Image (cartoon, rainbow over all chains, first blue to last red; front, side, top):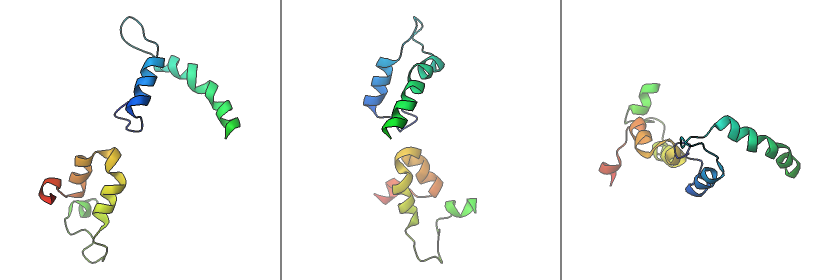
Length: 48
Length: 48
C-alpha cells in the first residue's frame, strides 16, 4: 500500500478493514478483487 | 544519453539550466526524493 504511493494512510486502513483474512493474518487479492472491483466497474461507468 | 543525467553540467549549452529542479518537483513525491536526487546527480544536504 505505501510502496504504491498513490494510497494515503486513510485509504490503506480502510482497505485493511474491508479486507478479509484467515487465521494466518493473510488475505487473498484474487478473492478481494473479484469481490469488489468488478461490481464497481459498470456502476462507475454509468456515473461517468 | 543515460550518462548526461548523471553529468552535473546538464544542458550546459541549453539555456534552461533549470530542468533538474523542474523534474525534482514533478517526480519527487512518488519515485523517492533521495533516489531521484541521486539519479539526477544533485545533493540536498549540500544545497541546504
